[PDB]
Image 1 (tube, each protein chain N blue to C red):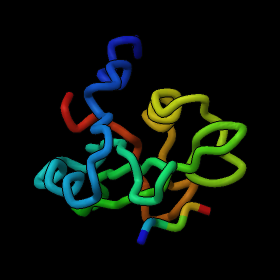
Image 2: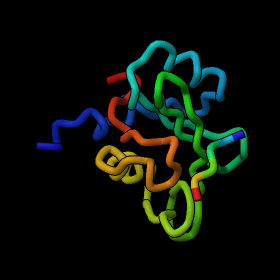
Image 3: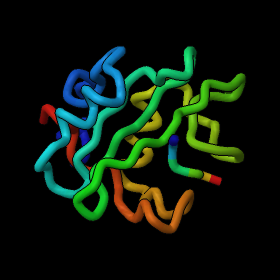
Image 4: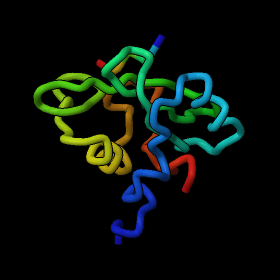
Length: 6
Length: 109
């Protein structure tokens, strides 16, 4: 689980 | 000038193949904007771990033909240190409204 960076 | 920044010494923030758990250990109790870079568990990618609002946030760093970055159209940087130098003066808010910090303070500065 990583931050969404879009 | 900004040549003084600790970010120019990659050893102040690059903690090699350290995993997520080790990253979280290292950042405990650190001020907002303290950060590190490492390999990701996703083999061949890297990750940035950064303290925001007192919590450690993890962001994958893509490795693409045009460079490293967090997302298109920002996969532009020729190295991790170019990425880090860019985000020392660019808030991560342009990627996620909940990441409104710069890569301010290398964990080992």
